[PDB]
Image 1 (cartoon, rainbow over the protein chains, first blue to last red):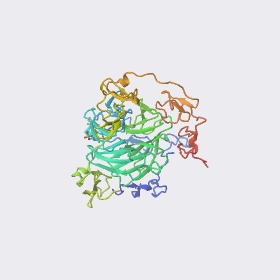
Image 2: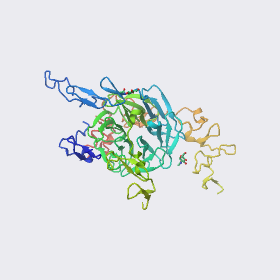
Image 3: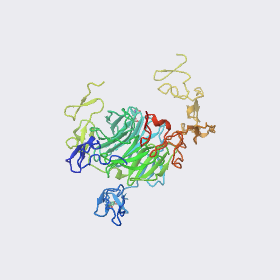
Image 4: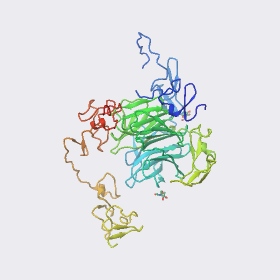
Length: 418
Length: 158
Ligand SMILES: *[C@@H]1O[C@H](CO)[C@@H](O)[C@H](O)[C@H]1NC(C)=O
Ligand SMILES: *[C@@H]1O[C@H](CO)[C@@H](O)[C@H](O)[C@H]1NC(C)=O
């Protein structure tokens, strides 16, 4: 594409440096740069008019369509993508062909799976040896659910039924909070808060590589978008004492702060891949916001102390977002666009930490560039932005104890480190 | 030494920690292979039905520490007690400061410190006010912590 992966696309079609998206100066004449970073209508309404209803703008209303909106001259068309059955002309419910979505959450000790309607709640797996589950992630194609246990300092995988529990990491993961699973490349992205690092491993833990650790102070959330090759994570207290919800390539190459305003304690992060938006909850400021992948059109979904007092983790599916709140100790439910009253999907005595929606649509299929003979890499083939690496979209990284060779595809033994 | 229990890894440990409930020896040997007639578990080690000795902290925690469930088989009445005027009694009978009440914070585990707070749209006399956010503590006004979303605190803090 004409616009680079680490660049923002002007309406005109010119690429702009990523830090300039909300730099404070309209680098894009089109004013696309700095387009409503701050978080602070109708049709038939005739502004100062007897009968001249405001033309407003087609498909320019926050919440006009659950998905891509086709702008019509005097109306709107709420188009729904593949696998999405249109409902009421405004909502894009999933295709019944795919099984009912499952809300996988941790009550505080054990990992629970329930139907998206909330009729029943079975326990997928009970943490043993006094352990507690914190973060959840899944790979639908392989029907595997991954969860971390801070008390046991271990990371576990299990089948969707609740059998064949496997231990993937137990060496140095002392306090892993959250996980993100790259279903396309079969890679697990792990956030370790014991030493404030983000490590990426295979589904079997075969190769471990530390990706982003430049200034991590207190990482709390993580999210990956294999289709576009992006990596989103949040820190509620950096080294400089500055919370930095940041977008970076899957290999953590072009780090860039995404939100730089009203960012108290960014706890959870989830990505709406269809609408290309980032939904992050703030535990301190008590608000769940939403910006695009470039952090341009900031929208406040739910705000207010009473409604969302202390969210930790948030997951999105269709027109609904499932966010867990520590203060209310409940897996609350909210509308994707705007909700005036959170819905209590489930309540637990302990404080819930993890939440995810188990559904085939949550992980759309995409090509894996690493399928081409491990991307020609001697070691870990890490996906990057589709545009990155001459458009190949993948990079070669070496495990611990090995160093990238001059060819950048081979791995020689390490020589010097302090 | 004479009073030091030898361990499989080679480390030593005072015989008090032997069966005390916690594996003071990092090889778990002090607690491993205990609970028998000769292996009398310590008072700190709450023994369960099948000689399952657990620390006294695990006496009646919510966690089913031992398979026999003796930790959960019987549990005594809690200590209701009371709290000071400044302290707020949470449902789990925990004394909590007024500023910690209604602060969008699960300050006391049960969360009753924040239960039913939306009924009032104002703020407490001892709690500052963040209209868009909450009734933060008055200490946050000039503590360098912009608790208020609007940044109402840390204003005019000369
Ligand atoms: C939904 O699933 C059915 C199979 O159950 C398939 O025939 C159909 O094309 C899918 N999509 C739509 C838009 O109905
Ligand atoms: C981690 O788990 C694997 C599989 O059970 C086991 O072989 C390995 O020894 C364990 N390592 C640690 C550090 O517990």
